[PDB]
Image (tube, rainbow, N blue to C red):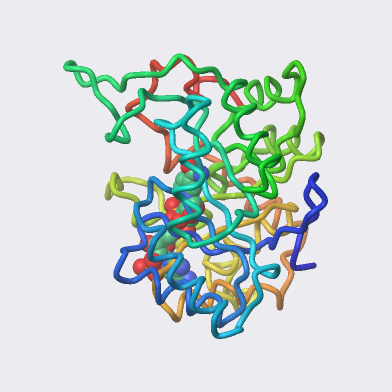
Length: 316
Ligand SMILES: NC(=O)c1ccc[n+]([C@@H]2O[C@H](COP(=O)([O-])OP(=O)(O)OC[C@H]3O[C@@H](n4cnc5c(N)ncnc54)[C@H](OP(=O)(O)O)[C@@H]3O)[C@@H](O)[C@H]2O)c1
């Protein structure tokens, strides 16, 4: 298992990164410091997470300490839905750069294909409770992303939560200048994503798997829902390999040529989650894990199903 995957912009991306959604602002600085100390070189961020300043404090301190050099880090962030207008994209990127206290991002993603009305609210609502869309299309937002590469603000651009028709729409864009480097999508044994992964990989787009542990801290979790970390079938594979269930869940996407971004703010788990370069799942283990697919999503953007660009009505 090599530590980095080559992107279609010519740069290498670490296959294991630290997620930061829901990492409390008073804990995430130490989490990122610990992560860098124990080997992580890739941090997955987003403006909508509201903690980029605190992530940035950690990055800056570890650079100052010379634990790592900037060239060795791979920092990812994402353009929120209220910034899809072409004229808002640069400033959104620059706010993230300023908060993360970086001069460039390694990768900047369109967070979702759905654009929303700009303004202070991340989910602007009409009086009837619906999320108000923007009229800016997926292709115009991509052209604005391309400009960021040409201005030196970002080394790579990509997409997130795009279905294959939406990926295809970008690939088929008239005058396309840069292909997406990455599509970051939810992926785990209950949402195995075979069709969309194969499509993206066939086009040279690297896939990053989010919520690889099934996001047991997601805000909308119910009692009722399936639980990867507690699934006896997965626990048995882990026991066979003398690893934790989380370590199996992280190794699984790695062996599919995916990047994976487990989140933790717990120092012991941050270290555990990195210790996934010391064992191999068999092909039979891999097929067995794939067999658990349920089409179950942590992140279904349920408030936005009427949006024209909602991604999850299409089969993939
Ligand atoms: N592009 C998108 O739209 C999108 C959407 C969702 C997620 N993401 C990205 O993907 C990252 C990961 O997904 P996620 O945050 O939804 O969930 P996740 O990584 O699947 O699960 C995180 C949860 O698992 C716990 N955990 C971590 N390591 C563990 C271990 N070894 N043993 C037991 N429990 C463990 C964490 O607890 P503690 O933190 O308390 O240790 C936290 O409650 C996000 O943080 C974000 O960076 C992106």
